[PDB]
Length: 61
RNA sequence: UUAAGUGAAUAAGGGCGCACGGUGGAUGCCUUGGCACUAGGAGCCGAUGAAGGACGGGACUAACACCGAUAUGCUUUGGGG
Image (cartoon, rainbow, N blue to C red):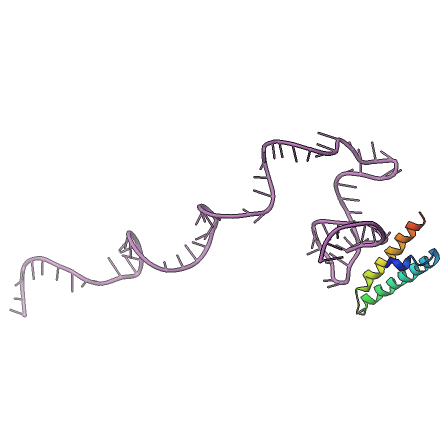
């Protein structure tokens, strides 16, 4: 879904990176204490972070 | 009845033949891996950090294969359904 990450600016990029890293922290705390019905969301967040970082590399030459 | 004479059978265990089992992995058939070559490519990598490794990445992950904090994967151009 890079078609939306290419509809933004390099400031909102770093903003959503902050948000997703925080989401990963909270997911990682759910999985340990006996919660988190939907365990497939940990991979999804990793991959959205990967996408933002590649797209930011591409545009700054 | 008494004398003189002749005397089988009976296996604690063993042998030979036969019948059925147990152990053990020979023989037959088979291939997932090898051996000797032919024709074609290629004949170097490295301070822009190598060859080879250590430690990590999975919902559960001891091991092997893959990958490197963007970690069981990210973008892009083509194929395929």
